Image (cartoon, rainbow, N blue to C red):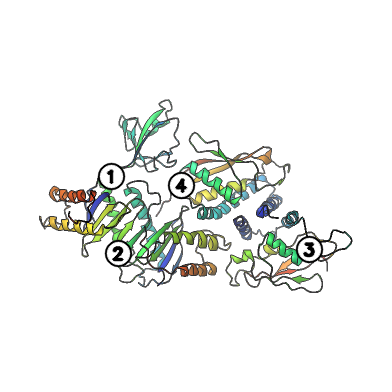
Amino acid sequence: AKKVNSEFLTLTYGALVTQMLRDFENAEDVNKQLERIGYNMGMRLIEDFLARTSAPRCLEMRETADRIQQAFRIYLNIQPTISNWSPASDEFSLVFDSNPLTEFVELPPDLTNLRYSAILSGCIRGALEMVQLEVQCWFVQDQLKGDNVTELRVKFVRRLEEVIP
Amino acid sequence: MTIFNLYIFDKFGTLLHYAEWNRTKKSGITREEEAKLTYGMLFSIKSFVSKISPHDPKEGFLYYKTNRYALHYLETPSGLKFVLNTDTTAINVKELLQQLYAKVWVEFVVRDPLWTPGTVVTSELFQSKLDEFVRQSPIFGIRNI
Amino acid sequence: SEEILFDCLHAEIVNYCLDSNKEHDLATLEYIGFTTGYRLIERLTREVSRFKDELETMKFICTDFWMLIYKKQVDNLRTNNHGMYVVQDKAFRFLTRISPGTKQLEHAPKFVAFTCGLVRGALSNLGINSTVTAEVQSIPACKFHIEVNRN
Amino acid sequence: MIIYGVYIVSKSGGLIFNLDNNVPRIEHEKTFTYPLDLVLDYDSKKVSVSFNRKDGINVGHVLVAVNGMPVNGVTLDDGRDVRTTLDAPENYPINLKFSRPKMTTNEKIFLASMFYPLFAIASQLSPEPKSSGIEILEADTFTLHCFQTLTGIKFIIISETGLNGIDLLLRKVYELYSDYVLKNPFYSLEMPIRCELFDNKLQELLAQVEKTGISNIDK
């Protein structure tokens, strides 16, 4: 009893993905819904992550990597391992052996372009812009699409700054 | 003799809420412009220190004091701002504001579905829970480090 | 603090409701969820021998499923003779975060669907059937009004 | 106890006197390789970094000298500009100096100017009635103590953050003020006080407080 309290979440997510996918025929449309809904979710989650980890704020991508992988530790109980840094330290890679949020959602649904981790991408970006870090997010490798490890990618695009006092 | 008041401001500089208990000097300014003025002032002080700092200001500004009252400031890395008024001299309250953020706000605001992001909180539970968390230590005085 | 994910996610579902249907929410969440909980319920109080059929009040199994998910106990459990009955609960988690003042009442059907959509059993009152309506008068106080799939 | 700087301003709020007690800014050099993780950003005469504050190169560390050759506002000494120097690869591997902009005097004037309202507008719409303004402003790595003359002039100094027993030191700098305004009361607020005699008397007050004695009111 209760190895995982929140295995509930992944099934809810599967419900949402199939509900949209029935609603909107295109993998692209649901991609935008996943991204924006991750955006709002990550906006919700980053403040709690900073209430617990109580980080100063991220002024350096090594710090950003440690912070977000710590959040994965504390939110999805996963241990992504930072790797593949940019020479300019913009890119780094998060090694998910098991995408926690999927437990054989479907290996073939007969649908490429349907990317699952887009919810993570939305969460990471919305979180980051709460802390004034506009970084784009995508997924270099993804088990479901035929890979062996699911690998998120983020590259430091711009340093947002508070303005207009 | 509980706290005077307490302020919230987003990373865009908008007043989220103002709760008052014991402020007495009846304001000639309607509260919204006052909140704007205070947010601008605090921003000014941030620039002020970030220029005239001898070295890295890791947390930058902390608070300011008067002879007859005092005030303290809290910075949230997301850019939300926390301000309350206290008396001049009692235990520090930087930690008390950290606690209020990490518990009361993160619970009774963001975990409220019917508070849309970036607006005024109007939850009777967030109101009453703020009232009770202040009534926790209705302590007046700061002497903050 | 794994709940925060689900609180936020259900919150955003409370947000978007497209006008095509009120509840686009199908129940596969409920089906696969009770199957999961019953993976954790690899033991429930029914005798080893197959003929002697004992029914488990899905009221009780609902109590336990809340402890597995909703974590807080169902309180006031009034029941008619036949499969129609109700639960009266003073506190509901998703409505614990809303103001207790009876002002935000609409947000219930997303709540009550989640307790529907659980596969039946042949012997009635066996613990798993579900088809449920809600009438939330007071905010924390959900009122899940049950109707069995049968009479 | 070390004092980073000492200041006084007038009824105008203009910076009348800005002696600094020699507190240098940090510096860094490192043999830079191919394009640097320091996120260099040009912002209006500042050639700085916006991110990746590594190795003790803060974000605010403005580029100060390039490869030994000095660098000036946006371009360099020799006429090269930071951009052309940087993005050309084969120059690398190279050293870059970096430090924080010691705000040139005029900028300090502007800083004092902008601060004065905060003093005079320290929530004059206070909670507490018939209140009084700011006196003590602690900060990250400095602390500001001001002494109103109780009518008129303001007395603000910049001290080590973790310290007490400085307001009496402000009273003594007030005494030095009286000593000097004895010189020429015509030599008033309108002109700033730059008279090296009183000023070395102040630097002797500094000399005393650099040593242990701040008790022993001796100045």
Check disc 3 and report the residue beneath it: C127
Q: Chain of mark 3?
A: C
Residue depicted at 21% across the width and 65% down the height: D151
Q: Quadrant of the N terminus of chain B?
A: bottom left
Distance, label 1 to label 2, CA atoms, is 29 Å
Residue D129 position (above or below residue A72):
below
Other-residue count near label 1 (Cα within 10 Å), few / some / many at <14 / 14–19 / ≥20: few
Depth check, front residue: B70 or C117: B70
Check disc 2 and report the residue beneath it: D133
The answer to which quarter of the image holds residue D170 is: bottom left
Q: Secondary structure at mark 4?
A: loop
Residue type, mark 2 in image: Gly
Indicate the position of residue B140 as horizontal and vertical percent values: 39, 68
Distance, label 1 to label 3, CA atoms, is 76 Å
Distance, label 4 to label 1, CA atoms, is 31 Å
Residue type, mark 4 in image: Leu
Closer to the camera: disc 1 or disc 2?
A: 1
Indicate the position of residue B127 as horizontal and vertical percent values: 51, 68
Query: Which mark identifies residue D23?
Result: 1
Q: Quadrant of the C terminus of chain B?
A: bottom left
Marks 1 and 2 share the same chain: yes
Q: Assess whether mark 3 and mark 2 are in contact (beta carbons under 8 angstroms).
A: no
Q: Which mark is first along the chain, 2 or 1?
A: 1
Closer to the camera: disc 4 or disc 1?
A: 1
Indicate the position of residue D92 as horizontal and vertical percent values: 41, 27
Other-residue count near label 3 (Cα within 10 Å), few / some / many at <14 / 14–19 / ≥20: some
Distance, label 4 to label 2, CA atoms, is 35 Å
Task: Pick out the residue farthest to the top.
Answer: D90
Other-residue count near label 2 (Cα within 10 Å), few / some / many at <14 / 14–19 / ≥20: many
Task: Pick out the residue farthest to the right.
Answer: C51
Q: Secondary structure at mark 3?
A: loop
